[PDB]
Every structure is written in structure tokens, then in C-alpha cells.
Picture 1 (tube, one colour):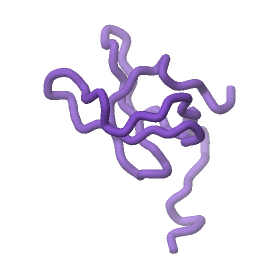
Picture 2: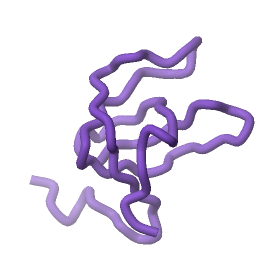
Picture 3: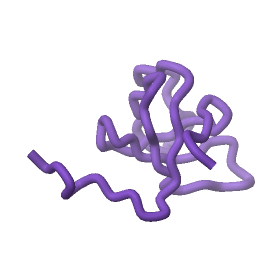
Picture 4: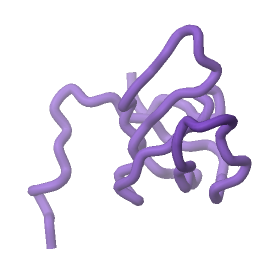
Length: 78
């Protein structure tokens, strides 16, 4: 019951997952928990790096953040 109160789209990045990962494979070292990605889920770019082969994001479906490759996903709109 949080309609039009949790969904904020004002210049925030969005991407649509292409693969379906369910916590596997887990991220290397102590980076953080994994996020459930499904083909058709929009995720916002929380933290992106350049010298890192892993990136962090936040799924709007699970409302949680996790580590995953940027290539495994494709931008929803640009």
C-alpha cells in the first residue's frame, strides 16, 4: 500500500535484467549479499566503479541491493 510513495523516477538510472539469477553465483570476497534478478526487472545504478569487475544496484521488485555484472544486464532506456 505504498503506491506513489516509494516509486521515484526523477533522473534515476534504470536497467532491465536479461538473465535470471537466484543468489547464484555469489559475489567474491566480502562485498555484500546477492540480489535476485529476473528477465523484466528494473534496477537502479546505486554504485558503479571503473577498476572493479563488479557493480552494485537496487531492484525495484525486491527492494534490495546486491552485486552483479553490468554486462549481464541491459539498459531499459537511454
